[PDB]
Structure formats: C-alpha cells, structure tokens
Image 1 (tube, rainbow over the protein chains, first blue to last red):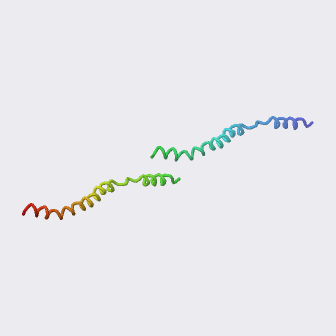
Image 2 (image 1 turned 45 degrees about the vertical axis):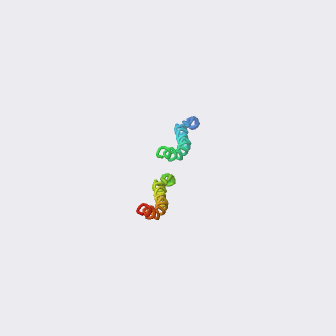
Image 3 (image 1 turned 30 degrees about the vertical axis):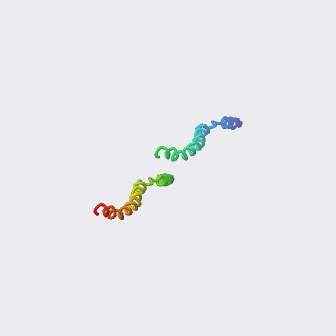
Length: 53
Length: 53
C-alpha cells in the first residue's frame, strides 16, 4: 500500500493557485496602474504650473 | 523638480519695462523740450530787448 502517497499528490495537484496571484495581478495592476501614475507625475508639476501661473 | 525656477524666470522675462522708461521719454522729452527751452533762453533777453527799448 502506497496510495495515500498518491492521494496527497493529487491534493498537491489540485493547487490553490493562490489568491497571491490575482491579488498580485491586482498589484501587478498596481505596477502598471503605477505606470499610469508615473505618467501623472509629469503632469503634477505641469498642471500645477498652469494652476500657479 | 525645478520648474518653479523656470516659472520665476518667465516672470522675470515678462518684464515690466518700467513706466520709468516712458515717463522718462517724457523726461527725455523734458531734456529736448529743454533743448527748445534753451533756445528760448536766447530770445528771453532779445524779446525783452525789443520790449524794453
């Protein structure tokens, strides 16, 4: 008898595929969301520039 | 960030061009207006000369 050793595999086979993937496509999103933010960084002072002058 | 240093330039670039230029073309005028007056200075006594004699 070994099957419970196979059972535990197929328990490992059914993986979670952690929410630490989709919370980190949401924070990979935070990466390229930031890529949008880093654009905004340029306009921060330029928009400001119009706003002040 | 430095742009406000550029802003302040373009605030210096837009200069007043002081009214102390056109009030002093008006007083540069007072210079050559005086140049007309200094002519008149000669006639002061000569006109007077006719007026008295």
